[PDB]
Image (cartoon, rainbow, N blue to C red; front, side, top):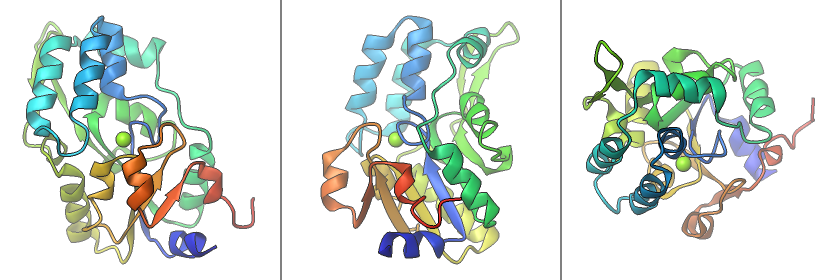
Length: 221
Ligand SMILES: [Mg+2]
């Protein structure tokens, strides 16, 4: 109930995407589509937390993947990421109370906009990395000016949102240490373990849930 009191005081909620809003890690699923799952999935685990600089870890994984525009399109069409149970209902209840909902990801806007356009979250509220392609569709790099291209990028996004909209109370929700480290500048953090529990987050977060229903413990409508 104290959790729900906190949750209901927020005027903006930012969700991590990989392993929070969706069950999978987008970059790993792209690597699967492109045939380099094993190497990239390992590098993704390697980059967890501030362990290695994020921009370098992103460049190296994409250098192995080399995703074409057609391959990104085929991922979205044939193997779309699975939404975590409860997230559709939770975003719906937040939007019905006019809480501004955002998605923040070190993954890619192509995929995250598809996810947002399952949750009625406008593309303006999506912050993610942007893949580049040549005219023929070949992988051409990524937008290195995005805040999500750098370590600490989630906190930079939240700072931008505070400066643009002056929200009173922004809550960050995510599964990983990089989400926990986005508070501050977020006003509170809720850790999420419904897909995989990151024990260091569970052990140190003030607020932690394993099923989005727990925030749907209000009046259930
Ligand atoms: Mg995550």
